[PDB]
Amino acid sequence: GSGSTLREVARVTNVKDTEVIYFSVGAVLSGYKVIYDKVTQRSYFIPELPTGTTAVSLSSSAILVHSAGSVDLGALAVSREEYVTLSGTFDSGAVINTKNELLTHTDGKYRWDGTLPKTVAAGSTPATTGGVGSGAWLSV
Amino acid sequence: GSGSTLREVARVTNVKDTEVIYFSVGAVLSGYKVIYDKVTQRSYFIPELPTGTTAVSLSSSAILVHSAGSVDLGALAVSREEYVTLSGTFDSGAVINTKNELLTHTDGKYRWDGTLPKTVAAGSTPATTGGVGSGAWLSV
Ligand SMILES: [Cl-]
Ligand SMILES: [K+]
């Protein structure tokens, strides 16, 4: 439903029901902890924004633009160790859209630190798709 | 409910609502990412199966048989670091049914790498129920 979807996000993020808010242009973001993107069906913690700040846009790269600037919500999720593990592997291929998305390789997972979105072809490894390091793949 | 249960699994697994499917005999598994077992009330990511592949059986040890083969969904969950922490501890005893279930000890958690199911009696430790190592308890 409508109010029930936010309560389910609240249980996963461990905040109160009143602290989750859908993204929508013009919505006041101050006073809330978690925002939910209805299109991508992903949730993110948001920083404490100045009172009255309203939402402008939320990209598929998890960049939230608002009336006081912007914030990379995927990058903020990384600092909070809040990750999404995509289906598939480096073997199957995948598309990385955000900074807090993980792709499983063999012994561990990796996030992409470079340009987004990141297309990973089938039969790939981290070494053959950019290498491991700053601006490339980082283990998680 | 019925459609609401899949939405609640989708939030925990970070997939879209339309990418979760109940397990049922004959259900088409292609195009979906997460399967939900109504009996055990557990969810598992599934591999990308060929178009038209249908489900056959799903055991309490998370063994999925389908029209194109079979897969240990519990082992796939381990490779994706998707675990279930059972209630109780080694001291209280428990029953391990899947490869992605964890039992808590005083120093940390462990998964069972051997034959399933695995019964743990009260007052047990990893050392007295098989030891620690390949084919026995593995720390997680
Ligand atoms: Cl690796
Ligand atoms: K939920």
Image (tube, coloured by chain):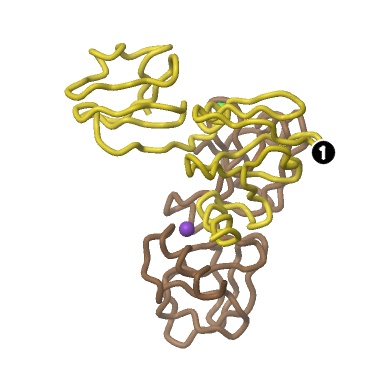
Chain colours: A brown, B yellow
Q: Amino acid at mark 1?
A: Gly
Q: In this orientation, which residue lies closer to the viewer: A55 or A34? A: A34
Q: Circle 1 sits in a helix, a strand or a loop, which is it?
A: loop
The x, y position of residue B97, in whole percent, is: 43, 27
Residue extending furthest right?
Answer: B51
Quadrant containing ligand 1 reads top right
Residue located beneath label 1 in the image:
B52
Relative depth, front residue between A78 and B4: B4
- Name the residue at the left extreme: B123
Q: Residue furthest bottom?
A: A52
Residue B104 is situated, as x and y percent measured from the top left of the image, at: 28, 32
Residue drawn 35% across the image and 18% down it: B137
Give the camera-side residue of B48 and B115.
Answer: B115
Q: Residue at x 73, y 38 (%)?
A: B26
Nearest the eye: B123 or B11: B123
Residue depicted at 59% across the width and 34% down the height: A104
Q: Please, which chain is the residue tagged with disc 1 on? A: B
Task: Tell me what residue is drawn at x 42 percent, y 12 percent.
Answer: B135
Q: Quadrant of the N terminus of chain A?
A: bottom right
Picture layout, residue A72 above or below residue A108: below
Tally of numbered tags: 1
Q: Residue B67 appears in which quarter of the rendering? A: top right
| Residue B54, x across and y down, in percent | 75, 36
Whether the residue carrying mark 1 lies under 8 Å from ligand 2 is answered with no
Q: Position of residue B73 (x, y in %)?
A: 57, 30
In the rendered image of this protein, does residue A135 appear above or below residue B93?
below
Q: How many residues crowd around disc 1 within 10 Å: few (fewer than 14), some, or many (20 or more)? A: few
In the rendered image, which quarter is residue B44 located in? Answer: top right
Left or right relative to A109: residue A120: right
Q: Is residue A30 left or right of residue B23?
A: left
